[PDB]
Image (cartoon, rainbow, N blue to C red):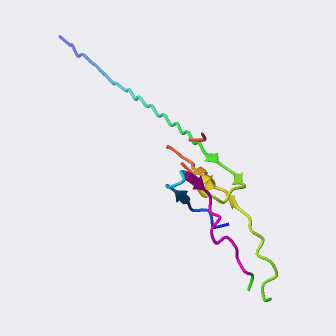
Amino acid sequence: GVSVGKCRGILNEIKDRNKRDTMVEDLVVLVRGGASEHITTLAYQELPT
Amino acid sequence: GEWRELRYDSTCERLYYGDDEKYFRKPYNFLKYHFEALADTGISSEFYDN
């Protein structure tokens, strides 16, 4: 009697994920006219109102 | 331009402006002082995310 069994197995799997996001915001003011404390308080760089 | 701080009068209930001692003598060697006022606040913000 002759009997011989052959079995071969192989597995492969790769998963990849990448995400990138950016957001930039700027605000510039320009005031000319006023010397009293009113323009000094208005010269606050920190809300455009 | 700097004589504008504050001025009050309680007896007559009179609130007025910086009229007291508002004059600046220009020291021959100076051509002109040219009082003016400008205040430019520029904010440059650049937020980057990677």
**In this image, A46 relative to A31: left or right?**
left
Q: Is residue A1 left or right of residue A15?
A: left
* B17 or A2, nearer to the observer: B17
Place residue A48 in its image quadrant: top right
Instruction: Report the residue at 50% width, 55% height from top.
Output: B11
Identify the residue shown where x is 73% and y is 86%: B27
Q: In which quarter of the view is residue A17 placed?
A: top left
Q: State the residue at coordinates (62%, 63%).
A: B18
Furthest-left residue in this view: A1
Viewer can see residue A44: no
Q: Please provide percent x and percent y for residue B1.
A: 68, 66
- Residue at the top extreme, as displayed: A1
Write down the quadrant of residue A2 in the picture: top left
The rendered magenta stretch, by its main secondary structure, is classed as loop
Q: Confirm whether residue B31 shows in the render.
A: yes
- Horizontal and vertical percent position of residue A10: 33, 24
Magenta segment includes B42: no
A31 or B45, which is in the foreground? A31
Viewer-proximal residue among B48 and A43: A43
Residue A1 locus on image (x, y percent): 17, 10
Q: Is B17 on the left-hand or right-hand side of A20?
A: right
Residue range in magenta is B14-25
Residue B33: give x, y in percent of width and height.
76, 75
* Rendered view: A48 above or below A17: below
Residue A17 or residue B18, whichever sits in front:
B18
Residue A14 placement, left or right of A45: left
Q: Is residue B21 magenta?
A: yes
